[PDB]
Image (tube, coloured by chain):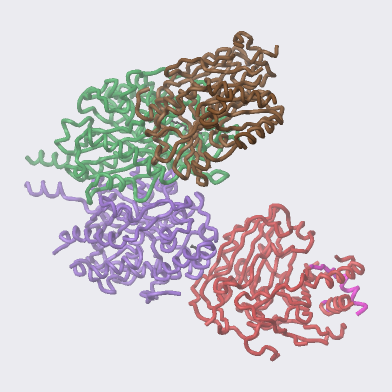
Chain colours: A purple, B green, C red, D brown
Amino acid sequence: IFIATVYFMSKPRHVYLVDYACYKPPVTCRVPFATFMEHSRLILKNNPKSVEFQMRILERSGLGEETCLPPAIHYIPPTPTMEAARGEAELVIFSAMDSLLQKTGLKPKDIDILIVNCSLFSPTPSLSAMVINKYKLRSNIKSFNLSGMGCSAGLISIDLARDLLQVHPNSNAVVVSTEIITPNYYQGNERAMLLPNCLFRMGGAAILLSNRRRNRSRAKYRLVHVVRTHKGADDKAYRCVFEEEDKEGKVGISLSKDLMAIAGEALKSNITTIGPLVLPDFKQAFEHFCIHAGGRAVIDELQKNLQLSAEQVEASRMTLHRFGNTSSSSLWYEMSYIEEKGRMKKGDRVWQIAFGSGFKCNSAVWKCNKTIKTTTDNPWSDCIDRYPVHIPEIVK
Amino acid sequence: IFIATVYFMSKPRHVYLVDYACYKPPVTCRVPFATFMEHSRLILKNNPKSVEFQMRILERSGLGEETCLPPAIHYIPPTPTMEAARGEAELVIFSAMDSLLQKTGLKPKDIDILIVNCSLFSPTPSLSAMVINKYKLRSNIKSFNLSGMGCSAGLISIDLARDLLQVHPNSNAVVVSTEIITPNYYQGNERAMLLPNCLFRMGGAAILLSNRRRNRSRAKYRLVHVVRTHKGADDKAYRCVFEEEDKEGKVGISLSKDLMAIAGEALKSNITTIGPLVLPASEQIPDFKQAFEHFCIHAGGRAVIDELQKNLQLSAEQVEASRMTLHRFGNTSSSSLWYEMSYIEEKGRMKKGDRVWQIAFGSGFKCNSAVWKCNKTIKTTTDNPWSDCIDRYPVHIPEIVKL
Amino acid sequence: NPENRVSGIKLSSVVPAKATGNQDYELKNIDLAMKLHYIKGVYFFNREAVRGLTIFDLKRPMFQLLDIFYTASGRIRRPAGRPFIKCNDGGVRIVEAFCDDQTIAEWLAMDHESRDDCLAYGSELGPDLAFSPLVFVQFTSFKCGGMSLGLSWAHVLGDPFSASAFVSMWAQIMAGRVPLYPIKRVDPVGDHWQFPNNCNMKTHTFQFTKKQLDQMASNLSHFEVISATIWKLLAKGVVTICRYNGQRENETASNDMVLSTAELSTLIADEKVLSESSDFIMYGANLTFVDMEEADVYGLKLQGQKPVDVNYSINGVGEQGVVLVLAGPEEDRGSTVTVVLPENQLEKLMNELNQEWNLA
Amino acid sequence: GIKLSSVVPAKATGNQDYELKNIDLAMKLHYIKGVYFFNREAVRGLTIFDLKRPMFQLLDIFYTASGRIRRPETAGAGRPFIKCNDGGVRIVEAFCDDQTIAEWLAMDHESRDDCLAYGSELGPDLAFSPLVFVQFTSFKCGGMSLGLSWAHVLGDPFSASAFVSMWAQIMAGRVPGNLYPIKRVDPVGDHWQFPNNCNMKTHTFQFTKKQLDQMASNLSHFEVISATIWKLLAKVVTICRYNGQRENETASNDMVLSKDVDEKVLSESSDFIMYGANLTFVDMEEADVYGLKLQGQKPVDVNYSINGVGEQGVVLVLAGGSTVTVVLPENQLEKLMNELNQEWNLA
Ligand SMILES: CCCCCCCCCCCC
Ligand SMILES: CCCCCCCCCCCC
């Protein structure tokens, strides 16, 4: 026997998405359009042009009336402090982690890898450190905290987990994708940097991954692929989403005018690297698509490029509507949507696309390990009945 | 053939430290003791007690007159802006990367993994994206940016690189570890977040790791072990080094009074966990000084070096690299270890088969050890951070330095 | 300057838990006829009632409460046409205030000029009608402790009884319970909806004890006694008494006031004026004697406690004056009298009341 | 919106000690202030880092210009000395977004150059008092003003001239009872400054070559100016002059007084004043102030001032024409002024 000695020994391990918990923002936090515009008028009294720009950007963003913002951003002078950001981080991360631990029955002593990704908020000790302290994790845990890597960092985390799971047998990896938006709020009137204020909302997700063979039946999905693209080499595609300062000393995320075109290119490259891998022309390769909810414009561009139907690009639109731009964790809200409509059959291929600053564009392919039953503990438990709502072209 | 094939497919890959370049601050930014104290008096005029505290903890800090700070703290008062922080990041990281690429002759396209490490500076796009744009790395590069993980993150990054080299055969991993000081300066006057102002100085390091067989004879070291400890479950060990705002609204790093005990406990647990892996069968208080040839203790301060020398019973000649790096470059954070190595390669002590034990402590409370084995006898060079001053060292570090 | 007694306030908004739906809400002719007047109701609570109560604890019941009062978070919209309360969830405006300088007792003992205008924050509707909050709720925390709840209520939304019901429902939900023309016509105001202050009329609060009220009634219920005394000591042609309809509970804000024009104690004891779309005013138009004695302001239950003082006042008063009569703080029933007069009339009333009961 | 930074020598000095001769201690109370002006073409976008870079090497040959005053541990009132603790010179960055170089050149008296050259007295905190302030004022037009505030204890005005001369060279790339003029005064402790008992004011004015020739015919620029000023004031004047020889001299003092009173007329018991003690007539005459080049452009104008002037008053004369700065205590300030206003319309 020589074929077995060269096949099984050098066979990649299977990485399973055992479960995940999405954060459900409090039902007493919504930020309606009218309240947002009233506060915006109050903050930008001396810049009516900025107010008009914000109104135009927010009235065609596809967001709903149930999106949530941190308590610190509630005051008409929004004063984001370090304590407020830490409190929001604790809230979201611990809620998602508690939901995950109750769902999976996982013990804190069983967590071998812990990867936390959150772009803007990078405290010290890290976010993974506060998770470890909260759950008293093992003293020999592989704790990683990625920051500054944008909205695609979510999938990056998954990739990292996968790699680690190939090196360490019988291990569990917890991946916490979030974006604490209290420090991300832009305290200025520069038009280019006011988009994140209009679009970004609260969210988060705690994901459990495992190569353990005992999870070959409990697992929801089985990670097939994680493709990555980094257009940072191109100078134009590097400055696309650039954190910087305005002419008044305020830090914000300036978005380039050409951010559309470059984004397109990146996506194309990714679908040129994921095509041959899944090739037995993508609307028939996969059964479900999770396009990152980065604004209805990019979703429309991807739909017109890949020739997706209204129902295929529906979890992304409805996730943008219900939760807004929850950043790297949005990919998971979309997942929940597909699961809760009773559309997650066994063997179904799910393709997640997450594109963000860098300019990075990553994608992942999962396969449904088991048919997913509709559940009550989830971020869609109440609003799933109304959806798919009719998102209007312009709201007032 | 069966057993041989099983062993070959089950044997872990070898990770090699092909080379590494350290940032050498120019001789225009050095901050003598008197100038630092004068700027402190000018800035913190309102609160004399804070100035007296800074003088007390800087006169016995064990630093020297050649430590460097970025060109934003030079002013009175400092004006740390995002542009200044980005400029310092470019100045340090691009210099270190250029030195690495010139030392190793590494083509940018040959870089497969890129792990950047900086605690308190986390721009968007990340520093790894900055490197990728500068050197036009590939679009399928495994790029990671670890931040918030403190001083020990330097040994976290390389650890990750190892875990990524054993999954991807025939690949290069560049690990950059720095600490940008401009977004690190406390602008308040509380006597708890001023010590990091006194100790921390600018520096960096870039490291090329590789599991390729061609980079095997020329490799400088072979990564033997990496042992990680995280005293984070304890609340005291978690809050010992905490980033928070003061009474006026200024972010800084508060250090608890019971920090020496926590750091000692973390070091003790780490050395206990690493003892079985390296100690010879003869020892198995087993002597750690009989298992390693060279030691690189993180230059976090004189107190920790004294504690380790008293516990491990290290002779004054084995903590020489740590003390001299602290004196020369100051507390360069995670990259300090990579300066200390360059001290034991320039005096000339890196013989083939030697064992190097690097211990880095930091917030979390994290504490990580690495054990390297000198692959080849390393010869002195003139493109090192110690090039212009290694002849004058080791110096006599006085207990108290008069102002 | 009493207006500076509070140094720094934090403003925020609170919205209904469930999106109302942006449905329209037509306003009756009576409502549009009182779109210039506003209610200021301040409740005081001692240190016991605020035992370990944070901002979130106070703001939590507001979401359910506004789910009930779906119009309290709406905004005025116009098609030139008649305004209507669009139910888009702009929310009510929450104002957190701190008064480290003084305590509740000092406020109770301080002069009443410009006294509670800084405890119940809130502007008028305009000149930006589309973005004008209809309700301002201010929680003020003093030096020694205790909390003051100041409600600024747009009268177009509802009558003062509706404001009292709003506060009562807030308290109950926090506890845990599960749910000579009488009306003058004036010049157009456009989209600012604020009566101009042609004169320098002043406001003042009088406190009457049970014994004083029963003693001064001999020369003439509590309301009739106070009204007759004020009329006799003020005129030294008609009076428009307002009574409202207190038969309401767990209902949305409504405006169902009852007028009674009397052409002096006997006059006190014993409707188509609005044409279609003019700008009207009746408070301070013909010496209105508004009352809230048929309310239960002191029946609030905060942490098993009751308010130590309730002050109700009217903004937008006309040229004549407004007399507000409210139940006193239990014990020996008293009476709080928040009244606005032109400076001269207020001075005469103060002199007469100081001569009689040494009240000034 | 000025910005203050420090510059330290590139090479550590190791905490040397510089003994201050009795002359330096006696004359420690005075301060030189020299302001030079440079036109648009002399700059063409000079970064402050580029300007500061030469200072790092320059301070190596002027190391004493980075130390701090100190007293011996033997006693609390010992002989002051310059400890080379590498405190560094104080670099000031200023931007004039309202006035141009020409506007400042035409700008008249009443503290024209005080705003153009930052300075401070050596005290009351001697241990942390910079000895040298170098201020770069960038005007909206484009020209710069270099203001050098130089403690006289460090050196004489010609020493500051040599300092700025070598700065410019290395920037270009070149490799580096009542008759006694000195009066004892009440000790000032550790705060080296002289309070003014009267209305002590200064005025600066320039004489063109034509008027200088006319006055010489009426009567060298030194003699003409001395006679003119003395006659105008009349209707002891001890003169201070340079030694007469120098080549890349370091920070020192080689001034000479004329009646040449011997320098052995003082001790270390108390403090002393020389400038302005008896109508001093400091005259630099020749100097490389205008001979220096920055990017090949000669300085448009240079002005020197003395701070810590004595009660009687001082006169400083430099080769421009000729620039004269006269500092007086009393109403003679106006008197002489009006005389000029009647002859050369100077006012
Ligand atoms: C519960 C109501 C919360 C309302 C939050 C409004 C946020 C305003 C953002 C202002 C954007 C300029
Ligand atoms: C070459 C100039 C070096 C100046 C270094 C001074 C740094 C200031 C530190 C301020 C600490 C209070």
Residue A27 is at least partly visible in this image: no
Is residue B253 shown above or below B376? below
Compared across the picture, whether B307 is left or right of C124 comes to: left
Vertical position of residue B272 compared to residue D81: above or below: below
- C206 in magenta: yes
Q: Position of residue C11 (x, y in %)?
A: 58, 61
In the image: residue A169, left or right of residue C275: left
| Residue pictured at 32% horizontal, 64% vertical | A335
Residue range (magenta): C204-222
Return the x and y of residue D220 as percentages of the image width and height. Answer: 53, 21
Question: In front here: B97 or B122?
Answer: B97
User: Hey, which quadrant is residue A261 in on the image?
Assistant: bottom left
Q: In which quarter of the image is residue A140?
A: top left
Please state the horizontal and vertical placement of residue B395, each as a whole percent of the image: 39, 18
| Above or below C289: residue D169 | above
Identify which residue is drawn at 64% across, 36% down.
D341
D48 and B261: which one is in front?
Answer: D48
Q: Which residue lies furthest to the bottom in this view?
A: C272
Q: Is residue A263 magenta?
A: no
* Left or right of residue A170, residue C132 in this image: right
Above or below for D250 versus B210? above
Q: Nearer the viewer, residue A252 or D108?
A: D108
Quick check: D180 left or right of A199? right
Residue A7 visible in the picture: yes
The number of callouts visible is 0
Q: Give residue C321's quadrant in the image.
A: bottom right
Locate residue B25, reporting x and y percent.
36, 31
